[PDB]
Image: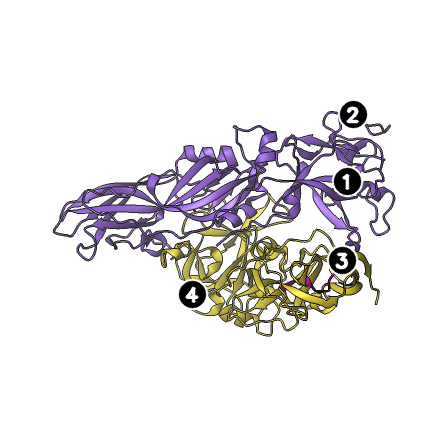
Amino acid sequence: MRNLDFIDSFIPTEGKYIRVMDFYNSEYPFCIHAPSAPNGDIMTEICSRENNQYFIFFPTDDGRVIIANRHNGSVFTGEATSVVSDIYTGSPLQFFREVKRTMATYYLAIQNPESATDVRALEPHSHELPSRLYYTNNIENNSNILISNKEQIYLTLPSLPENEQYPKTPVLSGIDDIGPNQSEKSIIGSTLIPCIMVSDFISLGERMKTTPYYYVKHTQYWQSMWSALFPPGSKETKTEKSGITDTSQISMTDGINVSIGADFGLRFGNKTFGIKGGFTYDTKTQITNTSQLLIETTYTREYTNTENFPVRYTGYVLASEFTLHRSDGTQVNTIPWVALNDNYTTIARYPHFASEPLLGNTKIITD
Amino acid sequence: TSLNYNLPEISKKFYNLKNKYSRNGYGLSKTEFPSSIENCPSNEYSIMYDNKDPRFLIRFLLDDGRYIIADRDDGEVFDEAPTYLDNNNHPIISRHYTGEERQKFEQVGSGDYITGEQFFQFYTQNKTRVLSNCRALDSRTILLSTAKIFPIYPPASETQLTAFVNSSFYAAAIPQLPQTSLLENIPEPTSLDDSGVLPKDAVRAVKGSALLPCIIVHDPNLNNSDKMKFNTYYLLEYKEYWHQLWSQIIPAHQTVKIQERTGISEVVQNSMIEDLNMYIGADFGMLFYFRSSGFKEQITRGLNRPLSQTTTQLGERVEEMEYYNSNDLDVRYVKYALAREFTLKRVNGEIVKNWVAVDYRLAGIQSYPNAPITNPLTLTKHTIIRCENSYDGHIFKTPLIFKNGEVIVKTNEELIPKINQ
């Protein structure tokens, strides 16, 4: 359609809107309120329209949610006997499960060093007065843990780019054509990432209001490594770079809490570990199966022209790049996050009917 | 918009697994001959190690990154038996898929990636046990898991018995993913006698699709060997269409009672459980049982249908609605609700089964004569006649106007009792 095209949107998923919460059984208009300070006790306070009372539920791979307030971006953190507001560190006590008992009412549960065991729900000790949120094992047929949404404001998400087809190998126009330094960049995939998991100069509280979601864009392209006119039957030695620089790995890790493994799979830190499955699916990448990090390696390779005529040859290496963007589209990272993979190479040639160069011996330079 | 389910390479190929250090080409084998090593007894279930009769194994990816290892020829999986051998070791045995912890393995890559000389190991029980050949590198023996783990940087002699590389392979059978399409507008009747479009003739829109590993699928038509070789992954399609609830001529200025049956019946739910260990929750999200649970997240991500947030099962919904025709003429009215359709197909395209859930939350009406000739129909009374659960006991606040071709979203309308308070 046009309208019906957004039929999926009419009934939104948990992390597409800002909400105001209240316990169903309270008769007086109490709302769940977060402290102005970055750390403090979560409380039921008289409902007002302040950002202390507005929350976004950020969903994770397994369906659990991270609950951040719109005033400062601090999240719900489970503690000994009470729920407090604190800075998101990816701690296990910062993941909650929303359970819908009915279409309109739900309760929030936290789980222990246990699995199927002690699921306890959040409950106030009063309906008449402002209260802290405590735990209870009394779940079944208990309406005191029951929460309702007073308000629901729909979020406008950034427009994500359309997925492109794998990058094609560059063509050469003549014997003197070295070819382009890079091929056209191809959008392989892009994914949405909560503002609380990214590094930026904008304050958390401000990100919550204007850019609650950031997005990571994944692109591929062919990078030029070398180019030469090979005389008939000549052997030449060309140098080919591979992997990721030390600065780029540090910048990426700092910026999105994601690193690249030696197998070219991705390594997720404590902040992003819970969303790794959604991240890799959207970007068409894989999770790493090794603990070694990808480093930078310089290789030498012998190439022999077997044709009886001179040939132009340009060597390209497959480049994979990640960019961090704000809701307004602006790019956050100033340092490039690029990994070159020397296992995937393509050799552009003139004339086109000429054979592939014969690959001889490969060495590694210890600069 | 095309689609990619994003399976890793090793989840798309049945590989022959050879030891990295063996000089005479020994690897994982289905050899009929028993173990030649004294302290390494073999039997009918033992996974063998030999340089003849190689096994071709696939690695199905679990949501937590662990793998299920299955054999191409007989469709059985690798299993860590609880029985003890010498030195507190467990034998690795062939068994039918159950989805238990003992069938899950963690792959860990190490070595010199820079020179392409890397290898991999299989671990169990939170990396406390490593899979190893029993005593030998170049002799027919068995496979077991040991709790005697050694350093990998200087590769101890014992570590060599745990190191694997990929060799030859067979392609798994992967069905092609269909392309998504848009949902059509609610179909208009062409005349007073036009009864509308029935579900059998309704135009479908593809919205999702997932690749289900054959081990979780119950397809009685095929034996486990044919199933694994020719139908390694089944295709599960997710579609939407406008499912007609009723079609009737309403006389001028008349109120009429109409029953609206939506949701899903128990028999259909039981069927989905039987075949896929999957079923629909009252919030229309997906629920899973033990045998398919390990793949929930990958499946739902592919389908574009969320994981359910309730434990309540969707059931049959029967509601009685009263409508009022305000026009001076007799009018053909027809009401459609959104159908959520799931289809299981084999690699060749053969349909195994269909399951439909009717979503009463998204529905609309169309008429003959159309607008602007006729005035829209009005809902004057809403009663819930029969429903086995109280997940959604809300009715519409009446009167409610149903504008031709407009979709009415139950959650965006005023209800009784009021929600979102």
Residue nearest the viewer, comparing B216 with B309: B216
Q: Is residue B144 left or right of residue B256?
A: right
Dominant SS in magenta? strand
Q: Which chain is yellow?
A: A
Relative to A243, residue A61 above or below: above
Q: Position of residue B77 (x, y in %)?
A: 66, 34
Residue nearest the viewer, comparing A170 with B4: A170
Q: Give the extent of the magenta segment.
A: A305-321
- State the residue position of label 4: A47
Residue A36: tell me if it is visible.
no
Per the image, label 3 sits on a secondary structure element best described as loop
- Do the residues under discs 2 and 4 have CB atoms within 8 angstroms? no
Q: Which chain is purple?
A: B
- State the residue position of label 3: A306
User: Gap between marks 2 and 1, in whole Å?
Assistant: 18 Å
User: Gap between marks 1 and 4, in whole Å?
Assistant: 66 Å
Per the image, label 1 sits on a secondary structure element best described as strand
Residue drawn 47% across and 60% down? A16
Residue B400's tag is none
Amino acid type, label 1: Lys
Residue nearest the viewer, comparing B231 with B388: B231
Amino acid type, label 3: Thr
| Residues beneath discs 1 and 3 located on the same chain | no
